[PDB]
Amino acid sequence: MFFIKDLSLNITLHPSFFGPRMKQYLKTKLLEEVEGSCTGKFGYILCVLDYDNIDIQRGRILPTDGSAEFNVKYRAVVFKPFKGEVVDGTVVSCSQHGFEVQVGPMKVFVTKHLMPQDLTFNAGSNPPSYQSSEDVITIKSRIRVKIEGCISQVSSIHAIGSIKEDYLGAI
Amino acid sequence: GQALDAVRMRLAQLTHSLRRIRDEMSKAELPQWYTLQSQLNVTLSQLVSVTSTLQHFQETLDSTVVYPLPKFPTTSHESLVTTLLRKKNIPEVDEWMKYVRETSGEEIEKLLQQDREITNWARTTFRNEYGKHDFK
Amino acid sequence: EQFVKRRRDMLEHINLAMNESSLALEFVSLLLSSVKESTGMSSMSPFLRKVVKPSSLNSDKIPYVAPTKKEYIELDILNKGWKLQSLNESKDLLRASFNKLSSILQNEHDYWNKIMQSISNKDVIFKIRDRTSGQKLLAIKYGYEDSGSTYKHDRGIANIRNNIESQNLDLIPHSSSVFKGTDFVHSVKKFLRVRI
Amino acid sequence: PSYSPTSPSYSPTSPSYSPTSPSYS
Amino acid sequence: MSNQALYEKLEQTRTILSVKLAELINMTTIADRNDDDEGSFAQENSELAVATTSVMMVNN
Amino acid sequence: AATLQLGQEFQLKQINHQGEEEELIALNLSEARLVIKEALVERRRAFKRSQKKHKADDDDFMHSETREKELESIDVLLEQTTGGNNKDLKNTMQYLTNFSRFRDQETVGAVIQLLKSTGLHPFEVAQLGSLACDTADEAKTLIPSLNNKISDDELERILKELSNLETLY
Amino acid sequence: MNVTPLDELQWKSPEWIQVFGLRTENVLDYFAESPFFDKTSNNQVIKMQRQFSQLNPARRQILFKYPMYMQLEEELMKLDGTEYVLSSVREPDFWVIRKQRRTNNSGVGSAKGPEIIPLQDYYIIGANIYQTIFKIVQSRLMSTSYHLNSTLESLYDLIEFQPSQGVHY
């Protein structure tokens, strides 16, 4: 879910970049390393605001290697869900065990035990989908999934959701 | 009240769009043609939506009866009350449709049905013309 | 001056159009304020907030008038009348637009044919962005740079300009950008003379 | 919330076009 | 590239056809239709906004 | 966040770098897409200004005729501002563009005003801006926080008005 | 034959206010000579009956304030039909009447009293009388559309096109 947060990072600048243009190198390093990353403490790093207003701190030369470490604070827009969240998304792949829904930059999987029995798997259809009396769900179909759990690793967060209750499926 | 509330919000956004197009036309320098087209089309389709929604809820608006507040003082705000009370059209539009009707000027009914048959015939003719050539 | 006059006219016309439209919002904003104060507070203008505490618009009921042949048939035939009007002005406006488009369009086919039948050909031709104008113009490379010359001062590049007055084609060199006139030919015509 | 309220566009200078005619008794 | 131009001309032609049919039907039934049967769907509720929608069609 | 369990990291009250408490800010697909597009075009303009310092066309990007032209402009913007090293950003931007309920800034402002006039939670407001529900009960079930907090008539009115506000493509 | 709508119709009676003056006692007397007062209403019948006999929220407040208003009910309950009754009064300049028609349905099975149904709105402001908002809104919108059409046709006249540049002014 999109939110604005205050973030900080420690960036090490190599001694070979020690010149009058160090601020430019720091800005390039920050933009090239932070944007698009994922942190389990704050979710995916989507965007950074006020690029011209980057805050900086005085260097502190490390005693072992000579690389100057800097502390940079900024404000960023990030995405992270919570337990019990309901989100609309796009069906990615269809399987017999369930389905996968892309929401934002993340994937939420639903197992066949997590939908009502009225939705039946049709493999002969192109592409294979889930068909019911009222709702049909397939590729590029907007589907609402109630996220139940999330697993966070260094570079990504996976999710598992359920649509077992009513008012779920095609919109 | 729900219908008038929807009318309120939609007309408020229409007035906001009018204020927008106003303060981007008031500049001494005219912007690019394309931005003007985008603003024109958006505001004009919004006016269409205004007309359609006002059409939809005529019964709720008609059922409502206008009455001044007991707390509202008319002695001091009679000018403001009269400002909103008045509804007569602007004169130029009035003589506009007067000249329009002047130019336009059982017989009328049979011309009306003749117009019906011309309309239906033209529609069928253009359907046939479209079907004649494969456009896919 | 006519452009200024018409701009002022359209400004005052749109102001007149919006003045009446504002009063509709001023009236309609009262109902929600009466029903819910906090949501309604922002809707009205500050002057109208100062005028009175807003509870103005309250729901009321009035019956629908009994129908008959009298007013619907005339309403609909007169709507037919205004839409026949709109069709008439539709045809007139479309005719005027198409006449203007045809006249202009045949004008640019006239210039287009002049360009097509005025241009000859091997020659290194490209599009370049003018330093002063910034638009794309045709340019021809005529220097000896690729023929083995080491003369670095001039690149031998000439821009093509269609003469508006004479409907002809002229070449303007890159270096001589100081002489701006019709006397360019004689001003730039140099020669080598040997005297014994 | 509310991005921006509407500017007051009152036109008191508008003369109005109320028809007056039934004054004589 | 050229295929994109092909596609663009495709929506260009289909848009011409669709707007042509739209203006044809609008001007032909510009004479408003009153039919007692519930099947017909032609509504002219507010008198002058009808002309406003007409000039809307014209300008579009 | 069925029970509005946002945790410490996403508390409603945020402490900024200035030390003053602020309301937590939540943006739907339209608001986030508009903000990121504005930031990217501003960064591109700054880059062009810097390049001109060392040594018109930008009006066409923000105003897009169609979804496909908008996507092409988005691809050009990513090529000229991002470098093509961030695929996740491209995927997020494509997801925003394909399923953006509202394209115009004024309509998005109207949606924001309609949703936050009642003073609901920012999470609920952003969810309503992201989800289009036909009936009030559908939204109430799909948004358990909205249960017991908003009258059904108000929710139905809001949903119908939002559905009417959707710009036809 | 062209008729001015009665909603905008405004009557002035300087002689009556000069002779009698504006008061709640004779506000109905002031209204009597107006065109809006139908001669077929039961109020006029009550007036001739009185003449022959002589010859031979704020609703409850105005209910309890005046005794002639009492006499109005005890003379109006017997006659059902179109009748003129006062709506509200704030002195010394504002009076509004309530235009309602009564059908005393005394049929078996209806425990309610006589049916009261609105017919028209009348506002007495000063010495002047005023009598649909839908028409006002549609009129304002249509005049706005006409002005917009004029402005846009003028602007399109100002527009000039060239193939090598596009459209300019």
Image (spheres, rainbow, N blue to C red):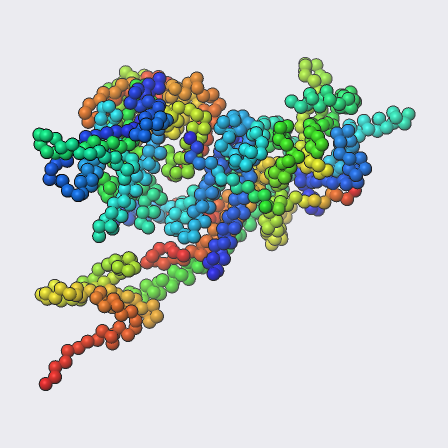
Image quarter hosting the C terminus of chain B:
top left
Q: Residue at x 74, y 40 (%)?
A: G12
Quarter residue F147 falls in? top left
Q: Is residue C62 above or below residue B104?
A: above
Going 75% across and 38% down the picture, which residue do you hit? G35
The count of marks equals: 0
Judging depth in this view, the residue of B80 and G163 nearest the camera is: B80
Seen in the picture, residue F73 relative to G162 is either above or below; the reply is above
Kindly tell me whether residue C49 is visible in this rendering. yes
Q: Could you tell me residue B37's position as x and y percent?
A: 41, 48
**Which residue corresponds to the image point at 28% horizontal and 29% vertical from the top-left?**
A6
Q: Is residue C6 left or right of residue C64?
A: left
Location of residue C84 in the rendering, given as x and y in whole percent from the top left corner: 55, 49
B5 on left or right of A88: right
Q: Residue at x 67, y 26 (%)?
A: G117
Looking at the rendering, in which quadrant would you find the N terminus of chain B?
Answer: top right
Instruction: Tell me the quarter of the picture where residue C152 sits.
Output: bottom left
- In this view, A1 is above or below C146: above
In the rendered image, the residue lying farthest to the right is G56
Residue C90 seen by the camera:
no
Extreme residue in the bottom direction: C196
Instruction: Tell me the quarter of the picture where residue F10 sits.
Output: top left
Q: Nearer the viewer, residue C8 or A5?
A: A5
Q: Position of residue C116 (x, y in %)?
A: 28, 65
Q: Position of residue F120 (x, y in %)?
A: 42, 24
Q: Nearer the viewer, residue C184 or A113?
A: C184
